[PDB]
Image (spheres, rainbow, N blue to C red):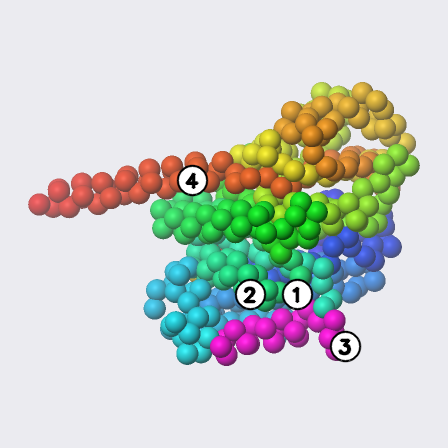
Amino acid sequence: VLNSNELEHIHSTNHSVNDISIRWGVIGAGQKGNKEADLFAGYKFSNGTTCYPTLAVNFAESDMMHLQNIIKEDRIHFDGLAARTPSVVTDLFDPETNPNANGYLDKLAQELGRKFTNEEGEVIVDQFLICLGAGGGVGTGWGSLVLQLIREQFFPCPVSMLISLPSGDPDEINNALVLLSEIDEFMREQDRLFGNSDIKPLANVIVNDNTQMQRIIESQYVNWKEVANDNVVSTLHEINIIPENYGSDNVTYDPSDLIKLLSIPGRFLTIGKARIAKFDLHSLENSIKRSLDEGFFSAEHQFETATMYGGFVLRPSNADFFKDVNTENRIRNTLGEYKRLDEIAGKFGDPIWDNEYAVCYTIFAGMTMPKRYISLAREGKELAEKQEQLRAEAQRKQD
Ligand SMILES: Nc1nc2c(ncn2[C@@H]2O[C@H](COP(=O)(O)OP(=O)(O)OP(O)(O)=S)[C@@H](O)[C@H]2O)c(=O)[nH]1
Ligand SMILES: [Mg+2]
Protein backbone atom coordinates (compact mmCIF):
# COMPACT_ATOMS: atom_id res chain seq x y z
CA VAL A 1 0.00 0.00 0.00
CA LEU A 2 1.36 3.48 -0.97
CA ASN A 3 -0.57 6.44 0.55
CA SER A 4 1.68 9.32 -0.52
CA ASN A 5 3.57 9.91 -3.76
CA GLU A 6 6.83 9.98 -1.78
CA LEU A 7 6.23 6.35 -0.82
CA GLU A 8 5.28 5.63 -4.46
CA HIS A 9 8.45 7.22 -5.82
CA ILE A 10 10.73 5.40 -3.33
CA HIS A 11 9.30 1.92 -3.95
CA SER A 12 9.45 2.16 -7.76
CA THR A 13 13.00 3.57 -7.47
CA ASN A 14 14.41 1.60 -4.52
CA HIS A 15 14.08 -2.17 -4.20
CA SER A 16 16.43 -2.45 -1.25
CA VAL A 17 13.94 -0.98 1.25
CA ASN A 18 14.48 -3.79 3.71
CA ASP A 19 14.78 -2.06 7.10
CA ILE A 20 13.54 0.92 9.12
CA SER A 21 15.12 3.23 11.66
CA ILE A 22 12.81 2.37 14.56
CA ARG A 23 10.90 -0.91 14.87
CA TRP A 24 7.55 0.44 16.06
CA GLY A 25 4.95 -1.80 17.62
CA VAL A 26 1.64 -0.15 16.72
CA ILE A 27 -1.49 -0.39 18.85
CA GLY A 28 -4.62 1.46 17.76
CA ALA A 29 -7.34 2.02 20.37
CA GLY A 30 -10.79 3.33 19.51
CA GLN A 31 -12.07 3.83 15.98
CA LYS A 32 -9.57 6.49 14.89
CA GLY A 33 -6.70 4.54 16.40
CA ASN A 34 -7.90 1.38 14.66
CA LYS A 35 -7.88 3.09 11.27
CA GLU A 36 -4.39 4.56 11.69
CA ALA A 37 -3.18 1.21 12.96
CA ASP A 38 -4.75 -0.45 9.90
CA LEU A 39 -2.66 1.77 7.63
CA PHE A 40 0.56 0.91 9.50
CA ALA A 41 -0.25 -2.78 9.29
CA GLY A 42 -0.43 -2.42 5.49
CA TYR A 43 3.18 -1.28 4.99
CA LYS A 44 5.69 -3.81 3.70
CA PHE A 45 9.36 -3.92 2.80
CA SER A 46 10.63 -4.51 -0.76
CA ASN A 47 10.95 -8.24 0.03
CA GLY A 48 7.24 -8.43 1.05
CA THR A 49 7.54 -8.81 4.86
CA THR A 50 5.40 -6.61 7.13
CA CYS A 51 7.15 -3.56 8.64
CA TYR A 52 5.18 -3.10 11.84
CA PRO A 53 3.52 -5.62 14.12
CA THR A 54 0.07 -4.16 14.75
CA LEU A 55 -2.88 -4.73 17.08
CA ALA A 56 -6.28 -3.09 17.04
CA VAL A 57 -8.10 -2.59 20.33
CA ASN A 58 -11.76 -1.63 20.84
CA PHE A 59 -15.03 -1.99 22.77
CA ALA A 60 -16.90 -4.25 20.43
CA GLU A 61 -16.83 -7.19 18.09
CA SER A 62 -18.80 -4.61 16.03
CA ASP A 63 -16.33 -1.70 16.05
CA MET A 64 -13.50 -3.58 14.26
CA MET A 65 -14.98 -5.36 11.23
CA HIS A 66 -14.02 -3.19 8.23
CA LEU A 67 -10.28 -3.28 8.84
CA GLN A 68 -8.23 -4.42 5.85
CA ASN A 69 -4.67 -5.22 6.81
CA ILE A 70 -5.31 -6.35 10.38
CA ILE A 71 -6.03 -10.09 10.62
CA LYS A 72 -9.05 -10.98 12.82
CA GLU A 73 -6.81 -12.72 15.36
CA ASP A 74 -5.11 -9.30 15.93
CA ARG A 75 -8.45 -7.52 16.51
CA ILE A 76 -8.63 -7.48 20.28
CA HIS A 77 -12.02 -6.61 21.82
CA PHE A 78 -13.03 -6.11 25.46
CA ASP A 79 -16.78 -6.66 26.08
CA GLY A 80 -18.24 -3.67 27.93
CA LEU A 81 -21.83 -3.92 29.19
CA ALA A 82 -23.64 1.15 29.92
CA ALA A 83 -22.23 4.62 29.09
CA ARG A 84 -19.31 4.73 26.61
CA THR A 85 -17.00 7.23 28.36
CA PRO A 86 -13.25 7.56 29.10
CA SER A 87 -13.67 6.90 32.85
CA VAL A 88 -15.81 3.71 32.85
CA VAL A 89 -13.46 2.27 30.18
CA THR A 90 -10.30 2.72 32.27
CA ASP A 91 -12.24 1.09 35.13
CA LEU A 92 -12.71 -2.27 33.38
CA PHE A 93 -9.03 -2.92 34.20
CA ASP A 94 -9.51 -2.14 37.91
CA PRO A 95 -11.19 -4.62 40.36
CA GLU A 96 -12.56 -1.43 41.88
CA THR A 97 -15.35 -2.21 39.37
CA ASN A 98 -14.74 -5.45 37.44
CA PRO A 99 -13.86 -8.67 39.25
CA ASN A 100 -12.74 -9.49 35.69
CA ALA A 101 -9.86 -6.96 35.86
CA ASN A 102 -7.02 -9.31 36.91
CA GLY A 103 -8.10 -11.56 34.02
CA TYR A 104 -8.75 -8.72 31.57
CA LEU A 105 -5.30 -7.25 32.50
CA ASP A 106 -3.61 -10.69 32.22
CA LYS A 107 -5.31 -11.08 28.77
CA LEU A 108 -3.88 -7.89 27.25
CA ALA A 109 -0.43 -8.94 28.56
CA GLN A 110 -0.63 -12.34 26.79
CA GLU A 111 -1.62 -10.57 23.53
CA LEU A 112 1.45 -8.42 24.25
CA GLY A 113 3.56 -11.59 24.47
CA ARG A 114 2.06 -13.06 21.30
CA LYS A 115 2.32 -10.14 18.90
CA PHE A 116 5.51 -8.27 19.89
CA THR A 117 7.75 -11.18 21.13
CA ASN A 118 9.51 -14.19 19.54
CA GLU A 119 9.23 -17.91 20.24
CA GLU A 120 12.56 -17.42 22.04
CA GLY A 121 11.04 -14.78 24.33
CA GLU A 122 12.83 -11.59 23.27
CA VAL A 123 10.81 -8.50 22.26
CA ILE A 124 10.81 -7.74 18.54
CA VAL A 125 10.17 -4.01 18.97
CA ASP A 126 12.06 -0.82 19.90
CA GLN A 127 9.07 1.26 21.04
CA PHE A 128 5.29 1.17 21.04
CA LEU A 129 3.23 3.55 18.98
CA ILE A 130 -0.22 3.97 20.45
CA CYS A 131 -2.78 5.63 18.16
CA LEU A 132 -5.72 7.47 19.70
CA GLY A 133 -8.47 9.86 18.80
CA ALA A 134 -8.95 12.09 21.86
CA GLY A 135 -12.64 12.77 22.53
CA GLY A 136 -14.28 9.37 22.33
CA GLY A 137 -14.79 6.91 25.16
CA VAL A 138 -12.68 3.93 24.10
CA GLY A 139 -9.78 5.95 22.67
CA THR A 140 -9.46 8.60 25.37
CA GLY A 141 -9.87 5.91 28.02
CA TRP A 142 -7.08 3.76 26.55
CA GLY A 143 -4.94 6.87 26.60
CA SER A 144 -5.37 7.16 30.39
CA LEU A 145 -4.97 3.45 30.97
CA VAL A 146 -1.68 3.60 29.04
CA LEU A 147 -0.29 6.35 31.29
CA GLN A 148 -1.32 4.19 34.24
CA LEU A 149 0.22 1.07 32.72
CA ILE A 150 3.61 2.55 31.93
CA ARG A 151 3.84 3.53 35.62
CA GLU A 152 3.28 -0.18 36.43
CA GLN A 153 6.22 -0.74 34.05
CA PHE A 154 3.74 -2.92 32.16
CA PHE A 155 5.50 -2.37 28.82
CA PRO A 156 8.95 -3.77 27.92
CA CYS A 157 10.06 -0.56 26.19
CA PRO A 158 9.11 3.11 25.71
CA VAL A 159 5.73 4.34 24.48
CA SER A 160 5.08 6.98 21.84
CA MET A 161 1.50 8.20 21.57
CA LEU A 162 -0.01 9.54 18.36
CA ILE A 163 -2.98 11.57 19.54
CA SER A 164 -5.56 13.49 17.55
CA LEU A 165 -7.42 16.47 19.02
CA PRO A 166 -11.22 16.65 18.58
CA SER A 167 -13.04 18.96 16.21
CA GLY A 168 -15.89 20.58 18.18
CA ASP A 169 -18.20 18.89 20.67
CA PRO A 170 -18.16 20.00 24.34
CA ASP A 171 -18.21 16.42 25.69
CA GLU A 172 -15.32 15.43 23.38
CA ILE A 173 -13.27 18.60 24.04
CA ASN A 174 -13.55 18.00 27.76
CA ASN A 175 -12.52 14.32 27.44
CA ALA A 176 -9.60 15.48 25.31
CA LEU A 177 -8.68 18.09 27.91
CA VAL A 178 -8.54 15.65 30.87
CA LEU A 179 -6.23 13.34 28.87
CA LEU A 180 -3.95 16.15 27.71
CA SER A 181 -3.86 17.30 31.33
CA GLU A 182 -2.95 13.82 32.55
CA ILE A 183 -0.18 13.84 29.97
CA ASP A 184 1.23 17.21 30.96
CA GLU A 185 1.33 15.95 34.58
CA PHE A 186 3.01 12.65 33.70
CA MET A 187 5.60 14.48 31.58
CA ARG A 188 6.42 16.76 34.52
CA GLU A 189 6.77 13.80 36.87
CA GLN A 190 9.01 12.15 34.25
CA ASP A 191 11.25 15.26 34.09
CA ARG A 192 11.98 15.08 37.82
CA LEU A 193 12.50 11.27 37.86
CA PHE A 194 14.81 10.89 34.80
CA GLY A 195 17.97 12.64 33.62
CA ASN A 196 18.30 14.74 30.46
CA SER A 197 20.32 11.84 28.94
CA ASP A 198 18.13 8.90 30.10
CA ILE A 199 15.72 6.91 27.94
CA LYS A 200 12.18 7.94 28.89
CA PRO A 201 9.30 5.45 29.39
CA LEU A 202 7.00 7.94 27.64
CA ALA A 203 9.18 8.59 24.59
CA ASN A 204 7.04 11.40 23.23
CA VAL A 205 3.55 12.51 22.31
CA ILE A 206 2.69 13.60 18.78
CA VAL A 207 -0.51 15.63 18.35
CA ASN A 208 -2.66 16.45 15.35
CA ASP A 209 -5.57 18.89 15.51
CA ASN A 210 -8.70 17.87 13.62
CA THR A 211 -9.67 21.50 13.02
CA GLN A 212 -6.33 22.45 11.49
CA MET A 213 -6.36 19.24 9.42
CA GLN A 214 -9.78 19.87 7.88
CA ARG A 215 -8.87 23.48 7.06
CA ILE A 216 -5.90 22.16 5.08
CA ILE A 217 -7.73 19.34 3.33
CA GLU A 218 -10.45 21.61 1.90
CA SER A 219 -7.73 23.90 0.41
CA GLN A 220 -5.56 21.46 -1.64
CA TYR A 221 -15.13 11.15 -3.04
CA VAL A 222 -13.88 13.53 -0.30
CA ASN A 223 -13.58 11.87 3.12
CA TRP A 224 -11.34 14.19 5.09
CA LYS A 225 -10.49 11.67 7.86
CA GLU A 226 -9.26 9.15 5.31
CA VAL A 227 -6.99 11.82 3.79
CA ALA A 228 -5.76 13.22 7.12
CA ASN A 229 -4.80 9.69 8.17
CA ASP A 230 -2.91 9.01 4.96
CA ASN A 231 -0.87 12.17 5.52
CA VAL A 232 0.09 11.74 9.17
CA VAL A 233 0.78 7.99 8.88
CA SER A 234 2.72 8.22 5.58
CA THR A 235 4.78 11.04 7.06
CA LEU A 236 5.77 8.99 10.12
CA HIS A 237 6.58 6.05 7.92
CA GLU A 238 8.66 8.24 5.59
CA ILE A 239 10.82 9.67 8.39
CA ASN A 240 11.35 6.09 9.59
CA ILE A 241 12.37 4.72 6.18
CA ILE A 242 14.66 7.50 5.06
CA PRO A 243 17.56 7.49 7.53
CA GLU A 244 17.88 3.72 7.29
CA ASN A 245 17.90 3.75 3.49
CA TYR A 246 19.54 6.90 2.19
CA GLY A 247 22.64 8.88 3.13
CA SER A 248 24.58 11.94 2.07
CA ASP A 249 27.82 13.21 0.64
CA ASN A 250 27.43 16.20 2.97
CA VAL A 251 25.48 15.31 6.09
CA THR A 252 23.59 12.05 6.79
CA TYR A 253 20.78 11.87 9.29
CA ASP A 254 21.36 8.29 10.41
CA PRO A 255 18.93 6.04 12.31
CA SER A 256 20.75 6.61 15.61
CA ASP A 257 20.05 10.35 15.33
CA LEU A 258 16.30 9.68 14.85
CA ILE A 259 16.18 7.20 17.74
CA LYS A 260 17.79 9.77 20.05
CA LEU A 261 15.22 12.36 18.90
CA LEU A 262 12.22 10.13 19.53
CA SER A 263 13.61 8.53 22.74
CA ILE A 264 15.24 11.09 24.97
CA PRO A 265 13.37 14.44 25.05
CA GLY A 266 10.21 12.67 26.25
CA ARG A 267 7.62 15.43 25.73
CA PHE A 268 5.65 16.99 22.87
CA LEU A 269 6.93 16.44 19.35
CA THR A 270 6.00 17.88 15.97
CA ILE A 271 6.84 17.35 12.31
CA GLY A 272 6.78 19.57 9.24
CA LYS A 273 6.78 17.91 5.82
CA ALA A 274 7.42 20.42 3.05
CA ARG A 275 7.49 19.61 -0.64
CA ILE A 276 9.86 21.74 -2.72
CA ALA A 277 9.94 22.28 -6.51
CA LYS A 278 11.14 25.89 -7.00
CA PHE A 279 14.90 25.52 -6.21
CA ASP A 280 15.30 28.99 -4.64
CA LEU A 281 15.75 30.59 -1.20
CA HIS A 282 12.30 32.26 -0.93
CA SER A 283 10.09 29.34 -1.98
CA LEU A 284 12.30 27.20 0.31
CA GLU A 285 11.67 29.48 3.30
CA ASN A 286 7.86 29.55 2.84
CA SER A 287 7.53 25.78 2.35
CA ILE A 288 9.32 25.09 5.58
CA LYS A 289 7.41 27.84 7.41
CA ARG A 290 4.14 26.55 6.01
CA SER A 291 4.73 22.92 6.97
CA LEU A 292 5.58 23.96 10.55
CA ASP A 293 2.75 26.50 11.08
CA GLU A 294 -0.02 25.38 8.72
CA GLY A 295 0.62 21.65 8.26
CA PHE A 296 -0.90 18.39 9.48
CA PHE A 297 1.05 18.32 12.76
CA SER A 298 0.54 21.98 13.72
CA ALA A 299 -1.25 22.73 16.97
CA GLU A 300 0.21 26.14 17.87
CA HIS A 301 3.30 24.41 19.30
CA GLN A 302 5.65 26.08 21.77
CA PHE A 303 8.82 25.92 19.69
CA GLU A 304 10.82 28.07 22.10
CA THR A 305 10.52 25.18 24.64
CA ALA A 306 11.98 22.57 22.22
CA THR A 307 15.01 20.72 23.65
CA MET A 308 16.07 18.89 20.49
CA TYR A 309 15.74 19.05 16.70
CA GLY A 310 16.17 16.79 13.72
CA GLY A 311 15.35 16.81 10.06
CA PHE A 312 16.56 16.35 6.55
CA VAL A 313 15.99 17.40 2.99
CA LEU A 314 15.71 14.50 0.60
CA ARG A 315 17.14 15.98 -2.63
CA PRO A 316 18.05 15.00 -6.20
CA SER A 317 21.53 13.73 -7.02
CA ASN A 318 22.64 16.72 -9.19
CA ALA A 319 21.22 19.31 -6.74
CA ASP A 320 24.16 21.42 -5.43
CA PHE A 321 21.79 24.21 -4.25
CA PHE A 322 21.09 22.28 -1.02
CA LYS A 323 24.76 21.91 -0.04
CA ASP A 324 25.45 25.65 -0.44
CA VAL A 325 26.34 28.07 2.42
CA ASN A 326 23.37 30.41 1.87
CA THR A 327 20.99 27.51 1.51
CA GLU A 328 22.37 25.87 4.68
CA ASN A 329 22.20 28.80 7.06
CA ARG A 330 19.00 29.97 5.32
CA ILE A 331 17.37 26.74 6.55
CA ARG A 332 19.43 27.17 9.73
CA ASN A 333 17.95 30.71 10.07
CA THR A 334 14.41 29.78 8.94
CA LEU A 335 14.24 27.00 11.52
CA GLY A 336 16.17 29.46 13.71
CA GLU A 337 13.06 31.68 13.97
CA TYR A 338 11.24 28.91 15.86
CA LYS A 339 14.01 27.75 18.12
CA ARG A 340 17.57 28.89 17.61
CA LEU A 341 19.35 25.70 16.49
CA ASP A 342 22.44 26.86 18.38
CA GLU A 343 20.63 26.54 21.70
CA ILE A 344 19.35 22.93 21.38
CA ALA A 345 20.83 19.46 20.49
CA GLY A 346 20.25 17.97 17.04
CA LYS A 347 21.35 17.47 13.41
CA PHE A 348 20.04 18.30 9.92
CA GLY A 349 20.89 16.13 6.91
CA ASP A 350 20.53 16.16 3.12
CA PRO A 351 20.22 12.64 1.68
CA ILE A 352 20.30 11.80 -2.01
CA TRP A 353 17.69 9.82 -3.93
CA ASP A 354 16.79 8.81 -7.54
CA ASN A 355 14.24 11.61 -8.03
CA GLU A 356 14.14 15.13 -9.43
CA TYR A 357 12.21 16.93 -6.69
CA ALA A 358 12.97 17.58 -3.00
CA VAL A 359 11.06 17.01 0.28
CA CYS A 360 12.07 18.70 3.54
CA TYR A 361 11.24 17.07 6.85
CA THR A 362 11.60 19.05 10.06
CA ILE A 363 11.21 17.66 13.57
CA PHE A 364 11.13 19.51 16.92
CA ALA A 365 11.00 17.45 20.09
CA GLY A 366 10.94 18.06 23.86
CA MET A 367 8.35 20.85 23.63
CA THR A 368 5.97 21.85 26.33
CA MET A 369 2.13 21.68 26.12
CA PRO A 370 0.83 23.10 22.79
CA LYS A 371 -1.27 26.29 22.90
CA ARG A 372 -4.17 24.56 21.12
CA TYR A 373 -4.82 23.22 24.64
CA ILE A 374 -5.76 26.73 25.76
CA SER A 375 -7.74 27.60 22.60
CA LEU A 376 -9.66 24.30 23.00
CA ALA A 377 -10.29 25.03 26.67
CA ARG A 378 -11.71 28.32 25.43
CA GLU A 379 -13.65 26.94 22.40
CA GLY A 380 -15.27 24.09 24.44
CA LYS A 381 -16.64 26.32 27.16
CA GLU A 382 -17.74 28.82 24.46
CA LEU A 383 -19.84 26.20 22.58
CA ALA A 384 -20.97 24.78 25.95
CA GLU A 385 -22.67 28.07 26.84
CA LYS A 386 -24.04 28.43 23.30
CA GLN A 387 -25.87 25.10 23.59
CA GLU A 388 -27.12 25.44 27.22
CA GLN A 389 -28.52 28.81 26.29
CA LEU A 390 -30.08 27.44 23.07
CA ARG A 391 -31.69 24.71 25.18
CA ALA A 392 -33.23 27.35 27.44
CA GLU A 393 -34.30 29.57 24.51
CA ALA A 394 -36.23 26.60 23.05
CA GLN A 395 -37.87 25.75 26.42
CA ARG A 396 -38.78 29.42 26.91
CA LYS A 397 -40.65 29.53 23.58
CA GLN A 398 -42.73 26.45 24.40
CA ASP A 399 -43.75 28.02 27.72
N1 LIG B 1 -8.27 12.58 12.46
C1 LIG B 1 -9.19 11.63 12.56
N2 LIG B 1 -10.06 11.71 13.61
C2 LIG B 1 -11.02 10.78 13.79
C3 LIG B 1 -11.16 9.71 12.91
N3 LIG B 1 -12.20 8.95 13.35
C4 LIG B 1 -12.72 9.53 14.48
N4 LIG B 1 -11.98 10.67 14.75
C5 LIG B 1 -12.09 11.68 15.81
O1 LIG B 1 -11.50 11.23 16.99
C6 LIG B 1 -12.36 11.42 18.10
C7 LIG B 1 -12.88 10.08 18.61
O2 LIG B 1 -13.42 9.32 17.55
P1 LIG B 1 -13.52 7.71 17.67
O3 LIG B 1 -12.31 7.03 17.15
O4 LIG B 1 -14.67 7.18 16.89
O5 LIG B 1 -13.68 7.46 19.26
P2 LIG B 1 -13.95 6.02 19.95
O6 LIG B 1 -12.75 5.65 20.72
O7 LIG B 1 -14.38 4.97 19.00
O8 LIG B 1 -15.08 6.42 21.04
P3 LIG B 1 -16.41 5.59 21.37
O9 LIG B 1 -17.57 6.57 21.57
O10 LIG B 1 -16.70 4.44 20.37
S1 LIG B 1 -16.18 4.88 22.86
C8 LIG B 1 -13.46 12.32 17.60
O11 LIG B 1 -13.08 13.66 17.79
C9 LIG B 1 -13.52 12.01 16.13
O12 LIG B 1 -13.90 13.10 15.34
C10 LIG B 1 -10.25 9.63 11.85
O13 LIG B 1 -10.31 8.71 11.05
N5 LIG B 1 -9.28 10.57 11.68
MG1 LIG C 1 -16.37 4.55 18.13
The three-letter amino acid code for the residue at tag 3 is Glu
Q: Amino acid at mark 1?
A: Pro
Q: Position of residue 88 (x, y in %)?
A: 39, 65
On residue 376, the disc is 4
Left-right relation of 289 to 322: left
Q: Which residues are magenta?
A: 102-122
Query: Residue 319 lies in what quarter of the image?
Result: top right
Q: Nearer the viewer, mark 4 or mark 1?
A: 1
Q: Secondary structure at mark 1?
A: loop
Residue 228 seen in the current view: no
Position above or below: 120 against 213? below
Helix, strand or loop at label 4? It is helix
Most foreground residue, 319 or 398: 319
- How would you rate the neighbour count of disc 2 (Cα within 10 Å): few for under 14, some for 14-19, many for 20 or more? few
For marks 4 and 1, the one nearer the N-term is 1
Choose mark 4 or mark 2, whichever is in front.
Answer: 2
Give the CA distance from mark 4 to mark 2.
31 Å
* Residue beneath the point at 33% across and 37% down: 382
Marks 2 and 3, the one that precedes in the sequence: 3
Q: Which residue is mark 2?
A: 152
Query: What's the CA distance linking mark 2 and mark 1?
Result: 11 Å
Q: Nearer the viewer, mark 4 or mark 3?
A: 3
| Left/right of residue 297 with respect to residue 10 in the rendered view | left
Look at mark 1 in the image and give the residue it sits on: 156
In the image, is residue 63 above or below residue 314?
below
Q: Earlier in the sequence, mark 4 or mark 2?
A: 2
The reply to whether discs 4 and 2 touch (Cβ–Cβ < 8 Å) is no
Amino acid type shown at disc 4: Leu
